Length: 122
Length: 122
Image (cartoon, rainbow over all chains, first blue to last red; front, side, top):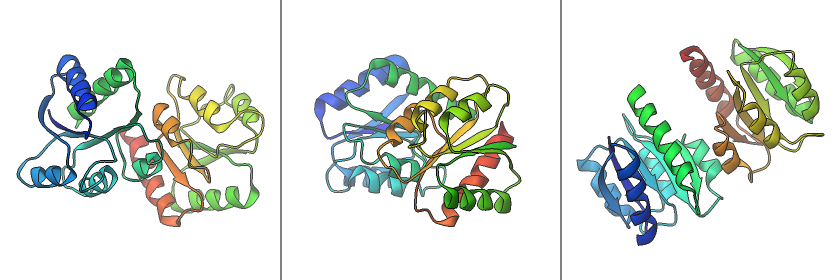
């Protein structure tokens, strides 16, 4: 299962990489601080799920997820953010989840288990 | 497929029930204007889906949906509401959708179809 993290804050992404590597067999295939990088990355790579915050550079996380959700064989989309204002837009684009920061290991851990199964099932 | 509508407000419940009757095969087993009457009704009837707004007498839409989501063989839950602030909670309880009022007819119609499919898959 290939995934990327789109998180402008080092501690946040460093944080998230750890729970994924420990609690799943997911291959994190990339991490990003810039929205444009992810755009460029996505033309030449096909991923299974993306974890993203929103207030990220060049191209914010809603636009990005909106765009990605138009893709054929699109990845799962999981927002992990301190801001609660974009959850409605997230329902509109059919996000897998919207996790508020600060979060608890178990929120993240159960989502990861749900997400693994959802990928499996498809 | 048996469904209930939970809506304070006559024109809104008429609109939504017209949409359901017209663009789906679902059966409206009941329309409730009060959260407690729903929780009682649910003690003697099993439903496949519930459509609800949030600011409803006696027992709020969020607490109700949280409760119902604990059930075995839980119905799908779909918020249809003018209030934007509860969509993070709706993700936490794993709502099927969360649609802002005023809505376009097509928003409802596409959701019914996606809802029908998810139910059949189930």
